[PDB]
Image (cartoon, rainbow over all chains, first blue to last red; front, side):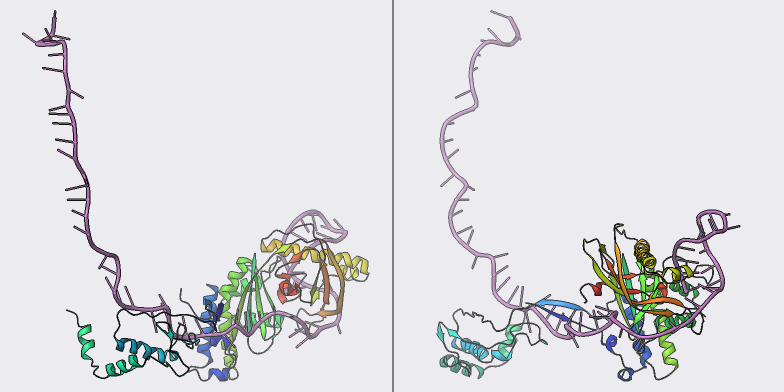
Length: 150
Length: 234
RNA sequence: GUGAACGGUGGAGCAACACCUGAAGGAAGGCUUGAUGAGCGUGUUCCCCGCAUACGCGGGG
């Protein structure tokens, strides 16, 4: 869908000087900004008041995601399922202010078997236990000599 | 070509001829060349030009508006706008609390195409009589009809010639009726007045695609309306 | 009658074997498609400009 979003200049939408009394310097500065944008309109410093379109996907359609692993430890799989439990807080898109990216996980397949419920993941208890033993004993030291350059 | 329309908002309605008088008075002291171009004066003296007015005032619900026909009038309007807007800003900030002056702009293109069927257009505040002979023609409908047809056709022709575009010369016009007859005044408190038609309806086989001005007193905001609104307005 | 005249550089031969371009990397962050144009006042001979050349036409405030 082509969804259209525009800007105004809201000082081109003031109208009443009682709204302008909040702006310091009086209405003369706002009128100077009016004269600035009309001088830009007759005439490359951009002002404001754009009109743009962006193509988005429609909402409510169902997608598939594939997260595969290459000889994983059970703690790594447990970390992936810990992320998949609370994926739904984050956003699978850009367009942060327009709420774009809200999603609900319909299912999660663990080598084909369905483990997803409404209250997170029901199943994969060995992976979760492995990752619970992995949060314990986790120090910043492993990250430090991972990031340290020779 | 194209005609540029500039809308000036002060929060209160002032009439187009009164705005013309008001605009001249505020800038009379400084920048006389800008005033000469805006009112279509001769470059030597105060007398206005005989030819088609490129820059004319018009009507705006919260103020007045400027019409600049062609590139020359658009440029005159383009350079005139900040000085005039600052003039209203200082004038309305001198007295009272102060009001935000609000501007708007449009660049309406002009077009015309000949069609083999009649089309209806209504014009309001239409001044038609300016000598005694036109008053003599208006007494009998048969000899006033052809005068009004020639006035409308010559108005369309002179506006097409002044804007620099070619108009087909096989156009036929027809006049149905006017709602009211009223006088206009050149200056307030003057005994002289000019007769005028109100809500006149005309039928042209061709179609018009922009702001078109017809008849006399074009610089006072008299007798022009947007045809682009009137296609299918009902 | 050229110190000439006459006279085959020939036969055979594998460039080929092996070898992962790619490991990591957020298209992002802000933004009224709603404004503008479509309705409201003047009551009779007076200043300038051209074609003419004044018998008048055109325009203009």
